[PDB]
Length: 138
Length: 136
Ligand SMILES: OC[C@H]1O[C@@H](O[C@H]2[C@H](O)[C@@H](O)[C@@H](O)O[C@@H]2CO)[C@H](O)[C@@H](O)[C@H]1O
Image (cartoon, rainbow over all chains, first blue to last red; front, side):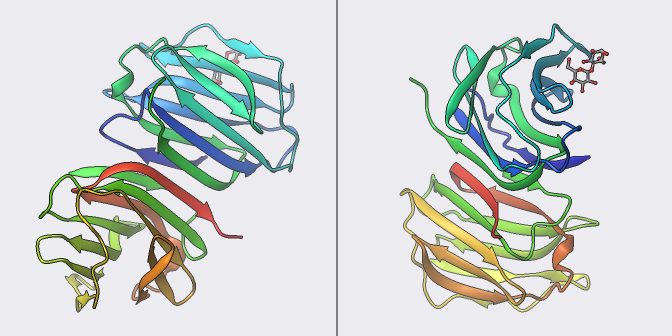
């Protein structure tokens, strides 16, 4: 189910950081953080830790379908243990830091960054905080 | 216009903080932060700093009408300068702070606190941060 959604119509990319703190309930489920663009609620960036396999799957949902999965074996999550995920965007990538360590970068596929106005968090995450902050560029 | 909206379907009241950082663009416009209840996006709490008169108005839209306005004694905001406002809810009030100093408390009128699932920010505020945190 949808756990959290935010809308910032002026565009929350590039140059914004999103920090999500929480924990899972289960050791076999998953959660996801999505950045959506208008029109059409296309998913510019989907970040999906899958606890059953301890893999992070990232992708984009453009033209009504997923593209190529980018799968990461770095999995700094454990069931029921609090975590902090920070996602920051520049002109070129989304950058993911978990528990203050850099984990991965995901190259933009949706180039219309300013049309990314929505953040969505779904499935097995008990959220303690969401922060959305303008951090500038380099 | 709508500047920001957040939805937490499990209910973001009581026992949550919302911290908004930003600044106004004008010397004499206004902005508002509204907490909305489900179903219907109903205005459980409306917080409205009005820079033309330098007055804060708080109210609720309940039983089909706006209630009695609470006009705050003080107006600590300065236009065109960054501020940090926090709204924290307990069982009895919304508590509002600027620079971590309390400005006012507003007694809950909508008692269905758990149905308050949305935060909405409208009009003259250039947002630099929104933080929504469960205080537990
Ligand atoms: O690529 C990201 C998404 O994957 C979807 O699941 C895929 C699955 O990973 C793949 O192995 C195959 O079975 O097709 C599935 C459907 O496309 C998820 O459903 C979706 O939520 C994204 O995570």
